[PDB]
Amino acid sequence: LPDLKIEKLDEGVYVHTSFEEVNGWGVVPKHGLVVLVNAEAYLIDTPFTAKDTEKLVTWFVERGYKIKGSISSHFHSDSTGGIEWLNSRSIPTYASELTNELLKKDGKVQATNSFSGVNYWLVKNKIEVFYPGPGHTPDNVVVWLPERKILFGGCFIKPYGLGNLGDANIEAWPKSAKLLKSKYGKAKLVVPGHSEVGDASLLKLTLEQAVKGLNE
Ligand SMILES: [Zn+2]
Ligand SMILES: [Zn+2]
Image (tube, rainbow, N blue to C red; front, side):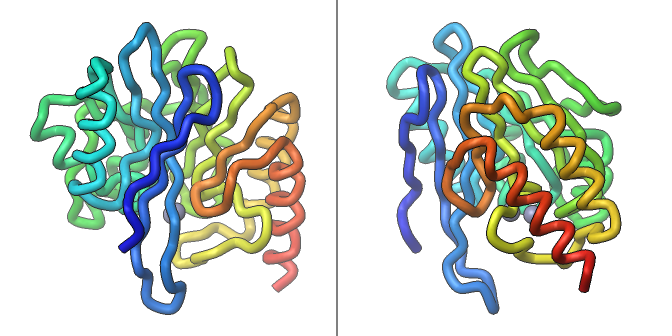
């Protein structure tokens, strides 16, 4: 029910926030990014719905920023819900091979472009994809913007509680978070999927929460 939000975070970097009512959770916000590269837009995660995906795309297109592509950080609908709509508009969609395998298992439309293995450049030296290992989901990836030092952690970054454990790997999450913290300690900003933007301390807080959740 709250409207899509689009807010500038940094030069060429915007945070989009969409909202869903989730049974037992109440209203759940979902953050992704729009990243501008030579005045074209890349969507980092789609909103939950085709409606908010269209609103997001239109906001940029009507301002002269063509959509070059989207990438989805994991198979959950809060990262993937707009894939069908983007595909229908011939906008390239990206997801890991494993994310696409889990979408297909969940009866969902797949991204048209897949990648495997651990580091992938969506845009050489500008938008990097990294797989830290299983945590929130088996397939969760993070997106790094090296020129800005901004990490989109997505639903893997859980600084105050692990959220929905439905598809989580509570055994692997601590090792995965330790690796992410080691690689991205230099981050200026970490953008979580469900919590507000913070600094690199969110990598430590996620590790602390994963360690705490394995204990039970
Ligand atoms: Zn999720
Ligand atoms: Zn999520």
